[PDB]
Image (cartoon, rainbow, N blue to C red; front, side, top):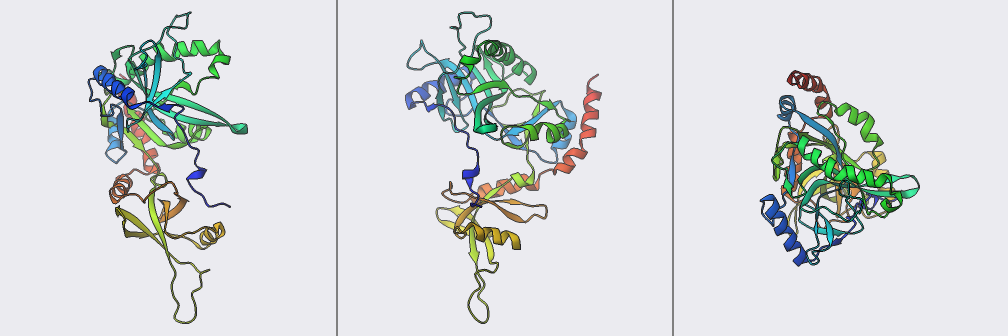
Length: 373
């Protein structure tokens, strides 16, 4: 068995080319003008970590819940090419404001038989995911979960119902019409676009047992979306991300220390100590914890026949709150910075266990129907 690394991870790549710097300046300014935001500042929302107080939040307001997809969070911008105004252009950009130009993509306009009209000043929020099919068939897909602007009109002040509603009618529906009668053309698309399916807030058990295990892309927990709130740029206290403790991983520097016995030479077959270190900055590392490795686990690590010491590893906390090896991270310059470590640990400390989340569901649902009067 080869040593597990990030090379095992199904990697999602934005199917496009980085837009040139001068083009990006135009796009940022243009987006800022429409939204009323700041050009250099990402206008998308960011969720907060689910904590204990959020059990009451779900009890007080209408919420949707869906699977938190593994993939890349991207906003989609339909506009004209900054250099060629006669050229329709689609951009996907992330929270670091990296703009990618996507080609061979097509978003039809309603009731247009020419297929030459196009959308401008339209901004979607969603996630690019990679669905796996049998025979190594892979399908890139853009799951839409919000709309900031459609056809020149900003919908950020409206609630989720109107926001997703306008996207479904003006974008998805005509696209659905086109796709049904143009499967040959559709296959050229770098990715397929669809509205992300959501459940009522109290329906997480259905997600756990029926939806999630049938997914064709990576899952990373749950996202809760309030339906009584406007779109918020930046940190949105109404938008909640929930993750099991095992998914709240941290990258450490691993060091092995073998005990020198009183008499004779060191038995290197014997279990050493597994020290986990945290990056303090530059080249400074400090001791943080011991990694728990059982006897059979130690045999597997030896079976890898790769260097174990002085390496970045990804670790998680088990049921007994012991740090456990998950995979090597050869894609990292350093371990997680102490500030990042503290932040992840805080999400866990304030966290709600899966069990406690489920036991709260009846109360949540009950209050949902008592609001429905």
